[PDB]
Image (cartoon, rainbow over all chains, first blue to last red; front, side):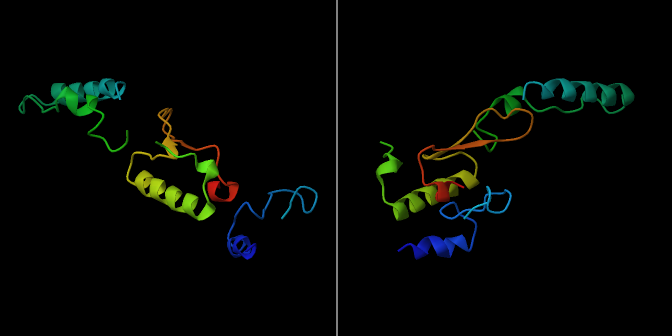
Length: 29
Length: 100
């Protein structure tokens, strides 16, 4: 069920994230 | 829209004074420019309560309408048109993943 997100996480989505930011401080998934 | 008429008129005067052998250089009627329908661009269920895969279909339908000009139910084309950059307004309450 959650995997649907992951399928679209391969593309850019918001469910998971690519905060255009410094790794692991504000950059996040 | 209205501001263009000035530009057009000054440019017409130059050809008119330059060339007098050919007379009455044509112009289009004013309503050709005034009429807004001629140019391309010009019961709603609460989307928050819906299931996800129906929001996707609705958004796709509105976007398919958006592509040809005028906007749709859940997404609007902002009427500002300031400078030359068009902008659009999606409904605020959506799924963030769909929204981006």
